[PDB]
Image (tube, rainbow, N blue to C red; front, side, top):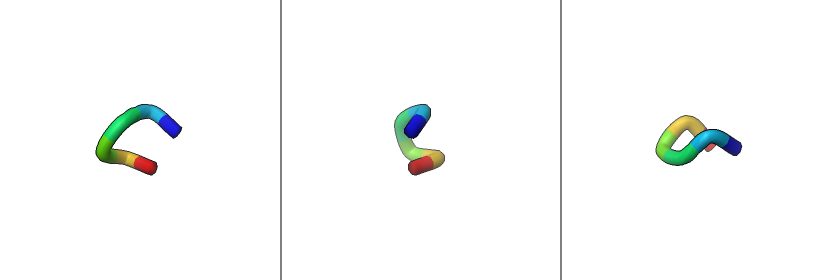
Length: 6
């Protein structure tokens, strides 16, 4: 949802 964090 935020970039690499998803």
